Length: 71
Ligand code: HEC
Ligand code: HEC
Ligand code: HEC
Ligand SMILES: C[C@H](CCC(=O)O)[C@H]1CC[C@H]2[C@@H]3CC[C@@H]4C[C@H](O)CC[C@]4(C)[C@H]3C[C@H](O)[C@]12C
Image (cartoon, rainbow, N blue to C red; front, side):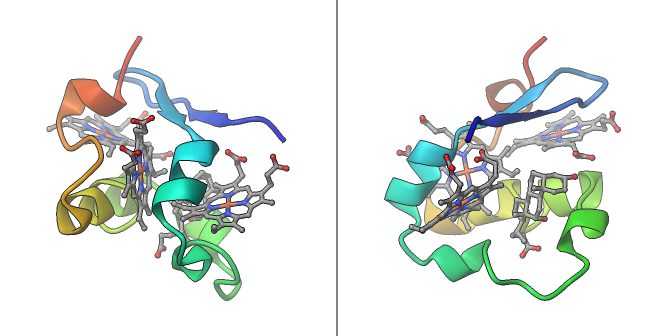
């Protein structure tokens, strides 16, 4: 499958799967979540535990605006 880009108005956000599969061997951090996670994602989740928050706790991954968002 292909990577996906989230069309954030301030700048597209790329999600590179290969890096995550390698760096987050606990697959259940993202997969086999109960229903609702597709509908549930948004800016609140992205800037929280959905993206940025995991990067902050992991001590690795982009945490600055322009490291995720890029026109
Ligand atoms: C969130 C940070 C994830 C983690 C950690 C893992 N996966 Fe994932 N996976 C995630 C998304 C959002 C998607 C769809 C969009 C994309 O970029 O591909 C996927 C996709 C997969 C797939 C399909 C890949 C393909 O056919 O190319 C597989 C087989 C898959 N995910 C498995 C997988 C495993 C085994 C993981 C742990 C090692 C893992 N993923 C981590 C989100 C996230
Ligand atoms: C943990 C559960 C994570 C979640 C959820 C998301 N990310 Fe992540 N990401 C995580 C780690 C530990 C790393 C380091 C990987 C590395 O090898 O440096 C990353 C990395 C990224 C990157 C950069 C990858 C690279 O090639 O350097 C990007 C661009 C990124 N992450 C984006 C991103 C987005 C948009 C997410 C939400 C949709 C997201 N990540 C979730 C851990 C985790
Ligand atoms: C990745 C780890 C991010 C960092 C760091 C920042 N943002 Fe972000 N943001 C990210 C994603 C994946 C999304 C999209 C949510 C979705 O619905 O898919 C967003 C969203 C925004 C938005 C709203 C965009 C829109 O609704 O169209 C804004 C205005 C925004 N982000 C700005 C922003 C700023 C100023 C940041 C640094 C302070 C920042 N983001 C960090 C991913 C990530
Ligand atoms: C469920 C995990 C982990 C975050 C959490 O604990 O909620 C999150 C992390 C990344 C999230 C995906 C980001 C890309 C997509 C954003 C869409 O708008 C809704 C579906 C997708 C495919 C999201 C589904 C789900 O919301 C995921 C896989």
